[PDB]
Image (cartoon, grey):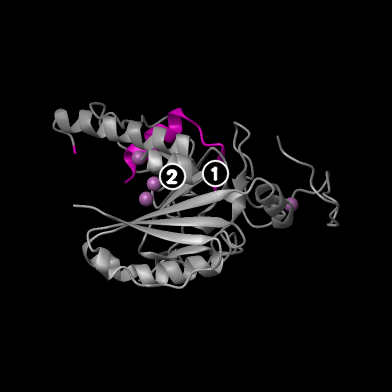
Amino acid sequence: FMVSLPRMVYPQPKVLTPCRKDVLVVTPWLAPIVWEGTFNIDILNEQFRLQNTTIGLTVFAIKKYVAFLKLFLETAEKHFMVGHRVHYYVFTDQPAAVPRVTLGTGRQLSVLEVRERRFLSEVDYLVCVDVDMEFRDHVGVEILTPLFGTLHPGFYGSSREAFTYERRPQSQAYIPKDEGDFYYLGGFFGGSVQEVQRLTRACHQAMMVDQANGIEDCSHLNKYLLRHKPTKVLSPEYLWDQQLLGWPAVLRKLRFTAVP
Ligand SMILES: [Hg+2]
Ligand SMILES: [Hg+2]
Ligand SMILES: [Hg+2]
Ligand SMILES: [Hg+2]
């Protein structure tokens, strides 16, 4: 049951004006592709707050990568799901090195030491990101959906033959030259807990099969998302490297970026 939205005043959507003429904003399976100018965040925030949505954010910080946690968390506090309930899950081999970062209300952090079902009872969505990154602009409930992937910032303009998919037929991750929608990158993906756990289970099983066959890019992610199409795709706004790629006109905002 979803309750009624309150009265809200905002500009009328214009049926005979595209919001972007420079980029594709829907996939051929009718999933939105999330670019700045496609969404009204006020509408979406209402829809999500009325469901009291909790977002989990998972990050692996091992060895020297623990050093990126402070900036990662500070900037998430500024930009990630602000106004909603957030549970950060930091997987680390160095629990005592996790910095003590001050969090907004309704936001919590758990540290899990490394050498499942918990997520189902704790959060509605899971977002899995790399820790060596920083938020620079809004990353909010516009991304939330059963299953989403993000466009590789190095390849969004490329033809699919150029995508660095797995190309050896003996690999479970094999995608032929004539197949492929997009090249997704593993730095930023998510969905419902159920969907994200399906994805990671399928990648893990295919990885075991390849290792069994003596075969060792985000190639499994890409095979999964070819075969189980995401319900949203995020633009490279959500996973950028300004050092390597600059700031092209097609990017109106740079939301989540590499840290040198
Ligand atoms: Hg628009
Ligand atoms: Hg995850
Ligand atoms: Hg991840
Ligand atoms: Hg995967």
Q: Which residue is mark 2?
A: 184
**Tag 2: Cα neighbours inside 10 Å, few (<14), some, or many (≥20)?**
many
Q: Which residue appears at 31% of the width and 68% of the height?
A: 98
Where's residue 110, x and y in %? 38, 58
Q: Is residue 36 left or right of residue 257?
A: right
Where's residue 157, x and y in %? 50, 49
**Which residue range is magenta in the image?**
216-234
Kind of residue at badge 1: Val
Q: Is residue 28 left or right of residue 154?
A: right
Task: Indicate the secondary structure of the residue bearing disc 2.
Answer: loop
Query: Are the two marked residues, 2 and 1, in contact with CB atoms closer than 8 angstroms?
Result: yes
* Label placed on residue 179: none
Image quadrant occupied by the N terminus: top right
Q: Which residue is mark 1?
A: 233
Q: Is residue 16 magenta-colored? A: no
Any part of residue 112 in sight? yes
